[PDB]
Image (cartoon, rainbow, N blue to C red; front, side, top):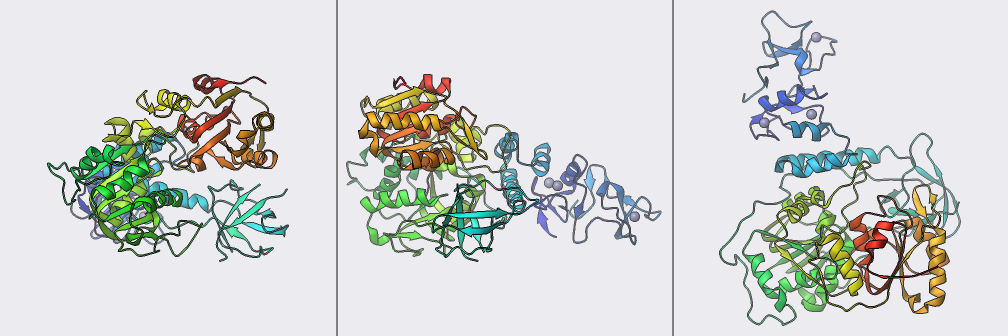
Length: 572
Ligand SMILES: [Zn+2]
Ligand SMILES: [Zn+2]
Ligand SMILES: [Zn+2]
């Protein structure tokens, strides 16, 4: 029971027994918490509870100290001092924002705003409390017992009565029962096991709630500005390919951490791997939340970096197939590519954290606890999609609230900004530049004249809650008959059930806007499906239309975003 106060560091025996994370609170601050919240259970070696036999008084404001023991108003001895008085809770070694984080349900956007505007220790307290709240919530869902097996990619499921039905999509990974992690999509429902097994009827699944470890390290280390490149050793022979980023690689060696905002196709992967060619002796650990993001850095490194000093770190609990061309689990190779939850405890000359909009403050803190670096580089875009906040249902989370790094990029600006998009046709670049980049993103490519927009609301049907718009897929089908060059297009939409219907009807490869992030395709066919807050989200709209290298067809539902699209309009 010896610890430091999560609000003002003053050492204390006190801990809130009512907080899901039981934080150490100092006498002055513990009082300010118990007197202003429903939280009244205070904990030392012994809890502050009435010592009188069979007495259930556990509220610290209704208790007193009778010698060395604690009693309520009904049991206290004549000579007894209140545990709560004079702005303090009695203990050893004798805030509004802490209260809100400690008592919120994490379903309002204002909870996440506070978790990002508060002091650094309160950001970790919020990131711990939120992750633990999300984990306990995973226990509320029902068990799915297999009723029948149709084939190798088809089954019929039976659900637990009295417990809600969890959303069936790639965002929810089940744990088969100990027959490996599994995933589900749409009475014929498709089954996707991260481990191959002959689907057993009766054998059930559950969403494995992984234990929330405490956070020790800050989301961001304190900034340090240096007058010379510290601990890194540059070249003068630096390939003309990376010539554009040498002033920015020098900025990287002259600061503890640095932020890079890179709109779609501005050269983030290229910048990250080119930092390794600029400091060729420096040991670089490349990290991201997703395997897809780490694999995209592995693919760019395979082209420029020597394959022998590269290692792709794979956790023993191999979930889904990833990058195979590097020596696996060699923690000591000069270039280590690894996800945040799999990071080994090591040090580096540079740490590169990619797709920073997908990081939570919990992930930012873990990276600072597992890796001790000379320089930390955060690459990403606050105009792209953030991590899914499964408890959040009320309000929209703005980019300045995704994490501490995004909060910085949106307020003080990024340290470095990649201003030229080399991927998209100018129609797409001009549209997103105006929409999310204050007209600072410039098009390298010319207008392709293959970017079309069609205003068609169609009919919205719902597979539980994920939406379908068959008339919009019907418009795509009609378009494909007249534009067969578009046969090579990737179908993109904000809903997996729309994608499921369009895969059966169009036969095009499917992708949600969220799963398309980081990827590029020559042709993209996008159906907005609905005009909800989800399908109208500007960061999702930005990601959807910036996937295309050559042409895009947008079948829109929202008049607003249709009007903003600087594409050739089509009739039908
Ligand atoms: Zn304190
Ligand atoms: Zn509390
Ligand atoms: Zn009592």
